Image (cartoon, rainbow over all chains, first blue to last red; front, side):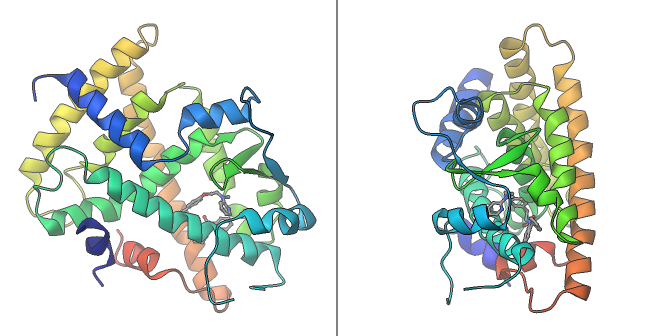
Length: 10
Length: 267
Ligand SMILES: CN(CCOc1ccc(C[C@H](Nc2ccccc2C(=O)c2ccccc2)C(=O)O)cc1)c1ccccn1
């Protein structure tokens, strides 16, 4: 998944 | 770039914005030198049950009859917010968001838990750990009394914290130190190591100057702190094995998707 990248992109 | 003190102050300012409970505030609570009331102490099943509703927790529902599983579930809620806090802090490190997005993910994947255990030391004394933004205090003996393998999780974190707290770092020191950890050019799978090492060079220079100014009596503190990075890797390694005993011998205990992603293919 890409959950960590979701917290990054704000 | 040339001014190391400006970098230190920028990181400290971001540190204060990202982490609600700093070491300074935690020390004021643990030593009782604060205006607010003492934390609620959680030392057994009854005191946990009495302080449970002050623990932040949003889910479908009553979760379980077992104390170990109750703490396991609540500790993973905290871990999720810690990753979110560290991610927020990481985006303020100068140059971090200019890196490849895949490398930002990689640096976070391997860095967050080393940072989590570093900042836990700020919330620990030899007898327990602060929880719920300093509102409660859960004793070391209680965490160690949990049935296997739950009683084995926190004890190595307490052992690390006693030795780590002996260095007497403060929030200004820790802000640079955790940035150094995130900007590790030797994380597995990094695509562009050179620009990462360029950032860590300034962070390391700022850290060394910060420790010399803030601890002029602590000779070779820079070297001692870098050696603690090896203590943190053993904690991660031991923690992953403890999670695997849980995964093989305990039932329904699936980790939060964010934690599963971090631990998946880790080392
Ligand atoms: C003891 N404590 C503060 C500890 O803070 C952390 C302590 C450790 C961690 C890291 C985190 N660990 C877990 C993740 C999922 C489930 C359990 C754990 C435990 O670590 C654990 C297991 C058994 C018994 C006790 C803990 C991670 O790997 O992501 C993150 C935060 C709290 C806080 C809130 C609620 C309950 N208590």
